[PDB]
Image (tube, coloured by chain):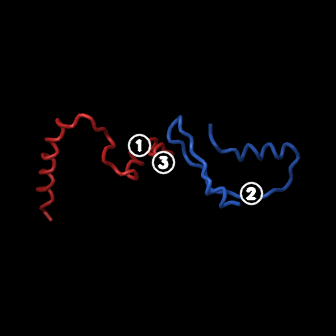
Chain colours: A red, B blue
Amino acid sequence: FANIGTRLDDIIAAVSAAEPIDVNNGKLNGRLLSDIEPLDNATYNTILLE
Amino acid sequence: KSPYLMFYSLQMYFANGGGPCYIVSTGVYDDWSDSETPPTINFSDLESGL
């Protein structure tokens, strides 16, 4: 243990450079289908019909 | 509208002269995702009741 917080705030700065270079991707990009059911239930049920 | 019609059909049956009958449930109601998406009815539940 105790290497967690050192490796975490490195990630916080590393993905901080990615926010001015993304121009087209929305909320659910790169997510699993099972993990969006608590997030947006109406979108998850619509994908199941298609 | 809601896709469930069982309670309404039993009202029509007893009003037209029905007697004793058998009930086979296939599951319980599902919730609406929002105000314009009612739940769906599955083919595999109705054939399991048969």
Q: Residues within 10 Å of mark 3 (few under 14, many from 20)?
A: few
List the residue tagged with mark 3: A48
**Are dots 2 and 3 on a single chain?**
no
What's the distance in space between the residues labelled 1 and 2, CA to CA?
Answer: 36 Å
Look at the numbered disc 1 and give the secondary structure of its residue: loop
Q: Inspect the image, locate mark 1, and give the three-letter code of the amino acid beneath it.
A: Asp
Kind of residue indicated by mark 2: Ile
Q: Residue B40: x and y, percent?
A: 58, 46
Q: Quarter holding the N terminus of chain B?
A: top right
Q: Specify few, some or many for label 2: CA neighbours under 10 Å numbering under 14, 14-19, or 20 or more.
A: few
**Residue at left offset 78%, top offset 58%:** B22
| Residue situated furthest bottom in the rendering | A1
Residue under numbered circle 1? A40
Q: Is residue B7 left or right of residue A24?
A: right
Q: Label 3 lies in what chain?
A: A
Label 3 or label 1, whichever lies nearer to me, is 3
The disc placed on residue B23 is 2
Instruction: Please state the horizontal and vertical placement of residue A13, each as a whole percent of the image.
Output: 12, 45
Badge 1: chain ID? A
Q: Picture coordinates of residue B4 (x, y %)?
A: 66, 45
Vertical relation: A27 (above or below) A37? above
Image side of residue A1 versus residue A36, left or right: left
Residue in the image at 51% along x and 45% along y: A49
**Label 2 close to label 3 by CB (< 8 Å):** no
Gap between marks 3 and 1 measured at Cα: 13 Å
- Mark 2, secondary structure of its residue: loop
Q: Secondary structure at mark 3?
A: helix
